[PDB]
Length: 226
Length: 227
Ligand SMILES: Nc1ccn([C@@H]2O[C@H](COP(=O)(O)OP(=O)(O)O)[C@@H](O)[C@H]2O)c(=O)n1
Ligand SMILES: Nc1ccn([C@@H]2O[C@H](COP(=O)(O)OP(=O)(O)O)[C@@H](O)[C@H]2O)c(=O)n1
Ligand SMILES: [Mg+2]
Image (cartoon, rainbow over all chains, first blue to last red; front, top):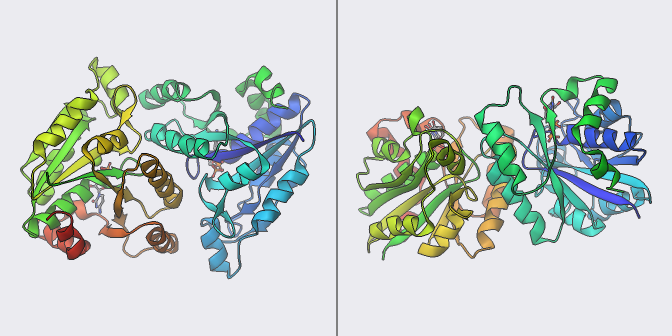
């Protein structure tokens, strides 16, 4: 076995996907082999595709997925809209265990938040993390309300003994503002803030994104993940 | 005593204050005596005042506050900015217990979400509900992400044996889109949906607000909140 992290967020559009790519890119430049798994992808009608973002931004090639639904809804609703079911629990857990190998960092990106339905029936990214014995990296905002949502996600993780590998602020504004600066300090009091990615990093070309990513995390911590 | 209800939300700006006003209004129209309590109010230098707004909307006059901070931040950050302290846990409980009375519905409006720190050290509204043996009414959105946020809040309540008095969709769009209608159907499988308040209800005058409020809640449920 290697290291499996689920990358979850406190909500939708907090930057989980940019974080997966950024940590992927930071680990790759540390000589770590990276694989990213997005079991369920929604919003394909408008072109959503988080694995292709990670491939473009970070250059991961081991990019694995099981289902893609057209509508920009939560997985369960997008599936009912399409008239089809979510994939089964065993599919996603086994896909991830099969990605896992010594010396490799495997990131599992969910859909929205920790407790959204990912597989039939009612199984979540938390259930999946329990099954593969993964730790969780939690992507937060620096905006108003983040302390509550972070604490809630962290309590839900710990309730099922899913270790917290730290926080990442998905989007750090420029200029910060009084709320973001206050929240960042307050976030660090409840868990390790591993990085804060600058707002707009997802528009960067691959070379600029690698530079940002290498600077954004601590070199020792990334190397220490595997 | 009577019935104490904390009114919390899955976030800030989900409609806690309008819900408080609407439930207060429906209970008042059922002949129930109502008090609305706001132990920690932030953003007062921007004009933020939920007690005053509950009074504007539903006519409530039994309105109790405790801490007020000028800056629109989390209570802990607003207090630091002002060089003031958060209230103690027992000061909040005293504020609520002074209001509690047989035959009375006392509503305690949180600040932001359920785990916002209201007192030191890290004392939250969940702790307060334990102290005054109140159930929690959870105000949610109908938008993307509400299911995760509602389930996270409900787990947090169960972890401390704080009963969930049900859900209220704070703002309900007319017409509802696909995502909103899906979320609503799914929220009703998670817990009782007590009401879904029409969007923009804060622009209804006293009469239209009161009518909206009587229709929004099941009369049996409201009447059953306090005997
Ligand atoms: N540091 C960041 C984080 C996100 N973003 C963008 O803001 C949107 C939300 O990010 P995301 O797609 O990773 O959100 P999740 O739903 O994956 O959590 C996306 O369109 C990002 O491209 C950015 O430009 N700079
Ligand atoms: N059904 C509703 C819900 C909220 N609103 C308004 O939407 C804003 C947020 O509602 P709120 O202040 O009660 O939200 P909280 O921060 O108290 O949870 C406020 O401006 C309300 O006046 C409305 O007009 N009709
Ligand atoms: Mg309010």
